[PDB]
Image: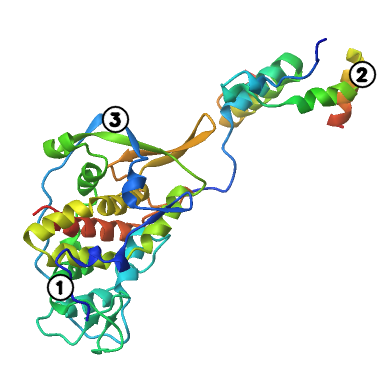
Amino acid sequence: RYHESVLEIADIFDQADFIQTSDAVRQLRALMPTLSTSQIRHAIERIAQ
Amino acid sequence: MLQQPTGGYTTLEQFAFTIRNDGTNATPTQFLQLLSYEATENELVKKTIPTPETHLPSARNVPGNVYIEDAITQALFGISAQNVNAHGYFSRLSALALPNTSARLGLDGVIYNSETINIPFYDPAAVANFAATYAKLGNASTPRYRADMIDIYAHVGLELAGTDAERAAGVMPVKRAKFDSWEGSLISLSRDVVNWKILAFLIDLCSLEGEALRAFKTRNRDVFRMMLFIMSTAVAANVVNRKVTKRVDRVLEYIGVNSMRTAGRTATITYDLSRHEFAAKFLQLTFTRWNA
Amino acid sequence: ALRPELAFDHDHIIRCLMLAAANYPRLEGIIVQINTGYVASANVIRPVSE
């Protein structure tokens, strides 16, 4: 009977200084394939490239 | 010729001084309410202002219509004002000081050597009283007559940020001003002030006497304080935003202490040394008239 | 006299230096290479054959 949903940290913390993002990035990460650490290195090496 | 009201020209709705507050019109008094101060370990003390030299600049006739109001307001409040110590304007001003001159001061703020019937103007006796003092602004550059550029700012601080007990005491802690503010709050404030018809204020400051004058001093203290505020932002050593919650608080350290900074900066209008000489001389004359 | 450029970000540069010191072996020798060059440019010590 639950409803699963994202909750931005901003909605609970009143201290704005330690809040750099939102639901957006998590939503983006949901699209990503689960990544072996080696794939993470490949990605970083590519963005660097 | 405009008759001068017993309360002074400043009583007229024609001469109301007002400033936008994040764009909405508001009296200077309801802007000064936003200001709050943090005291520091240093202490301002207001030693007495040296009395202004009697010597007015010579009343040489000059071609054209001097725009004296714009001259003064730009020298004090405008962004990067130039030629502030140029002598011609104040020479015509001293011509206004004469007992039966042909010259006239328009409500526009211009001086006309013509009697110029088409344009309304201040009562000549009043501008005689006013020019008799403010023509001295032409002395601002000459080495003999340069005003203390440093100590006078103590008074400014006291008259702006000073609590009533400190204003009685004559000694206040150096203060750090702050207020909820918008993108270019100080520049926009200087724009709102440079458009003020200050000659009504100055002419009233010089012409009125007794109870009407003292009532003028109480009725207009907030105005004087706003001009003082714009100067303080011009001389503040440092000005910075502080992000408190979602609000952004402008913070001017420090009120009442002229840093003698001359290089331009984003936050505020900036005085070249000529603007310091000018503003200091203006403060000498104005604070002398204000305290009598 | 203001220069039209961003402020040197101390709080961020120190952070990135720590992340680099964690992840980048070269960093030590990068920094050394500046100091070493400086010693050399101060011309303070030179070998002799004697």
Kindly identify the residue that appears in the image at 29 percent across and 73 percent down. Answer: B68
Viewer-side residue, A17 vs C43: A17
In space, the residues marked 3 and 1 are separated at their CA atoms by 41 Å
Q: Which amino acid is tagged 3?
A: Ala
Chain ID, mark 1 = B
Residue B69 in the image: above or below residue B256: below
Chain ID, mark 2 = A
In space, the residues marked 2 and 3 are separated at their CA atoms by 57 Å
Q: State whether residue B179 appears in this view.
A: yes
Residue C8 at x, y percent in the picture:
58, 34
Give the label, 1 or 2, closer to the camera: 1
Q: In this view, does B277 lie to the left or right of B25?
A: left
Task: Give the number of marks.
Answer: 3
Kindly identify the residue that appears in the image at 21 percent across and 64 percent down. Answer: B202
Residue B220 at x, y percent in the picture:
23, 54
Residue B213 in the image: above or below residue C17: below
User: Do tag 3 and tag 1 residues touch (Cβ < 8 Å)?
Assistant: no
Residue B126, numbered label: 1
User: Do tag 1 and tag 2 residues touch (Cβ < 8 Å)?
Assistant: no
Residue B71, numbered label: none
Kindly identify the residue that appears in the image at 12 percent across and 55 percent down. Answer: B214
Q: Name the residue under label 2.
A: A39
